[PDB]
Amino acid sequence: MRLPYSWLREVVAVGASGWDVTPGELEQTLLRIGHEVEEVIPLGPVDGPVTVGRVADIEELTGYKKPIRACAVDIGDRQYREIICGATNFAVGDLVVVALPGATLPGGFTISARKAYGRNSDGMICSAAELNLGADHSGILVLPPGAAEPGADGAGVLGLDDVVFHLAITPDRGYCMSVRGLARELACAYDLDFVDPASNSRVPPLPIEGPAWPLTVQPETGVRRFALRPVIGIDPAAVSPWWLQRRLLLCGIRATCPAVDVTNYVMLELGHPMHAHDRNRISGTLGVRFARSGETAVTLDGIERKLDTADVLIVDDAATAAIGGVMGAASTEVRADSTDVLLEAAIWDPAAVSRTQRRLHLPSEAARRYERTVDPAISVAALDRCARLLADIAGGEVSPTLTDWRGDPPCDDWSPPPIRMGVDVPDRIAGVAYPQGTTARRLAQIGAVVTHDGDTLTVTPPSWRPDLRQPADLVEEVLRLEGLEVIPSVLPPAPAGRGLTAGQQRRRTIGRSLALSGYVEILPTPFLPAGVFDLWGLEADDSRRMTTRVLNPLEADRPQLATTLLPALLEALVRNVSRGLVDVALFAIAQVVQPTEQTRGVGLIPVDRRPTDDEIAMLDASLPRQPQHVAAVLAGLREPRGPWGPGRPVEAADAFEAVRIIARASRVDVTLRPAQYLPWHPGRCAQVFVGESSVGHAGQLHPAVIERSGLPKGTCAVELNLDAIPCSAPLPAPRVSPYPAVFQDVSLVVAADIPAQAVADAVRAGAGDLLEDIALFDVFTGPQIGEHRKSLTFALRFRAPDRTLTEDDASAARDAAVQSAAERVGAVLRGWKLA
Amino acid sequence: DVPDRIAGVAYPQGTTARRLAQIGAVVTHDGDTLTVTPPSWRPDLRQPADLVEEVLRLEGLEVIPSVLPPAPAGRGLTAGQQRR
């Protein structure tokens, strides 16, 4: 909302004459009581000969791209100057504003008598924007007849010493979308007496003698008030005086004709939107009703609107007269020939206006005020104010008839219910001991009726403050007018908290451990890439395809939420690689979204109580499962090149080691088992287990997936479900025998299909507790042991808890380990030695 | 009432004066202030804290409830501590 300081000042000055403040101080006062000042715009300075002129001749220059005019302009004292101008929105006889040689316009533009378009031009005719007066629109500024004489000083006529304040009003303060509301706020901030410009001393009531027009209202439309009053015999050729056109311009409204200008003007002054109908274009009774399915209306911009059954209309016998509270209709619109006007002062349902205008994308000046609730007590004051102004400007007569529907039954008292509050509640909420009388004084200032009864205040807010419903609402009024800056800064005592949960600590430890091992964390987008699971070649019934879908994604082809973190990680990997960073290891820790059913919403639970435990469980059960995952991808060199050697390319074993890094960080033991699971390579894919629970997969990606997706060759990947890895808090008590150890190596031949870990497990089971350590040294294949067999050499370390092991006790334990391997995996002993 | 405050326990009336007599002290009342003269075999009873201990241990420490204090808004670990 835009308004000029002069207007605001004039309204404040009625009750406090002489009041006047600098723009900087006004800005600061508005910020501290809660109004955001987006911009302070002093009307840009002019200097030198910028004066009113009168166009006395127009010659059309031909031959150029555009139409161009050479104008004789009267600039005062019977002096005429030739001026070239490209605008077309003016005629001979019009008052305009000329910047003549020697003048300077805002932005440092000096005017000189240049030669333009073949003729000499002694200056220019100015637009409102070139004067920094108002919005840049097509054509130059034309002042209304009689506004000033040729030669009058531009700065003074235009009022260029004004300042326009551009505010962003919050939706709880609809009453501030007008000079009435902001001036009242200023009166509160500065402790002034305030004269309400909507009051009866300032808007004396007009006569009330018979209905102004037949009206039916279906009350379930939520209309609260609907008043009409006619003005007859206005001159359709009259234009608004300059003072009115100017204020409209500074508030961002272009003047068009008095009947419309006056409704816009009174809207800005008092905050009650107003509309002017051509009464001779109304056919029969005016009806307020909901639209029907499929119904259409043409608004006064000539655009056809598809209506909704929740849209409230004004109709007559023949057509729609308005989309109520949003925009008037073409059929009753004031036109160039309109002589008899019916003025509409209505109060619509805020939510109804809010839904309708957003559906139609019509955030009009009226709609935005009705959305935030317009004061229903001033409809006839605004109607009367607006009829007088129109009759005076356009030379009509105000008819003494008035329709004023005030509900079924009529409502004669508009203020909200009384609110009841302890006198010191604001002091407690603020942590400030305000002087006595403070909250009652501030609550009267904003217009409430306040009565005292011991220590409890009863507060009845005014009708323009529908936001004041509870004690907290009143606290805010007291605190913001006192100023939040007086509230001290006092650290509370927070309780003895328990710190981070075990899960929270684990997710920190996993991140630290992966980062130290060379992985770089990314923040993964939950919006899956288009067609990713077809690139992966997943089966139609793969659970990962069962995705929750977003209705309004920013990219139409990416509406599916991620069931797996790998797509986001591979997308970051491709990005790094395409920028020349080809040796990369990335990880992410984030939830996924895994629905178990079709989207099911749970109906509104009443908010005047807490939901029950069963309602909470039902809300939870309606959501997709959202477990925490950890995942990582690797490509390129795992070990970089340097003086030590050529480096080492990423291999599947690096993904297995990432599993082990995460398991150590989680303090759990994992086992890895061969698996076939896209998008992994079937021969280089491990499924990961904690106990007998599957927690995810790791290994090298499938070469066909790599190739279809444009991934680096040999890319490896890991994804684990953190929710499936049990919590663990071990309390170790390691036995540390100091007696000497015995070292032996053993080589065992097994079928090639036997996993090395199964052999190690068997060796461990047979050797017993004397076996302190076992490590796989060598995997050897060759023709002399059989084409489908392999030799595994294990280093064994034996140690007794209470004595020096004999080398023969060690060999007894080795014999038992060999036998166990023989019985469990069919191992055959090839040889052993002392290490 | 100093023992009551230190213990966080509201002992019955007459409790500290009764216990301090039991251990052999001469106890006189003057409004809310006790004057306590310990016996010659108790050279350890020199300050009010010494008398608090006598009252609290004969009543039994097990009657003292467990009440978490409000500790202030601390600043956490120093930069050096985090670095190490």
Image (tube, coloured by chain):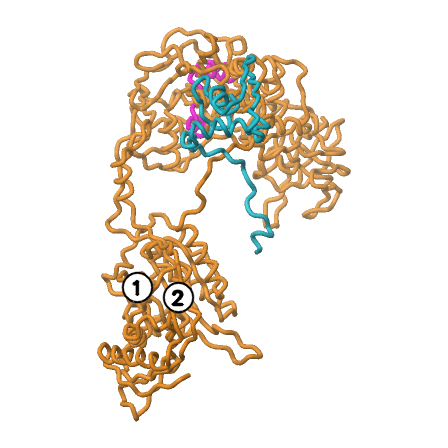
Chain colours: A orange, B cyan
Front residue of this view, candidates A704 and A404: A704
Location of mark 1 (residue):
A689
Q: Is residue A732 magenta?
A: no
Tell me which amino acid carries mark 1. Phe
Q: Residues within 10 Å of mark 2 (few under 14, many from 20)?
A: some
Q: Is residue A371 magenta?
A: yes
Question: For residue A157, which numbered disc appears in the image?
Answer: none
Q: Is residue A790 above or below residue A9?
A: below
Magenta: main secondary structure:
helix
Front residue of this view, candidates A54 and A642: A642
Q: Are marks 1 and 2 in contact (CB under 8 Å)?
A: no
Q: CA distance from mark 1 to mark 2?
A: 11 Å
Q: Secondary structure at mark 2?
A: helix
- In this image, A236 relative to A228: left or right? right
- In this image, A592 relative to A45: left or right? left
Residue at the extreme bottom of the image, as rendered:
A784
Tell me which amino acid carries mark 2. Arg
Disc 2: host chain: A
The stretch of residues the image draws in magenta is A366-391
Location of mark 2 (residue):
A660
Q: Is residue A526 above or below residue A446?
A: below
Q: Secondary structure at mark 1?
A: strand
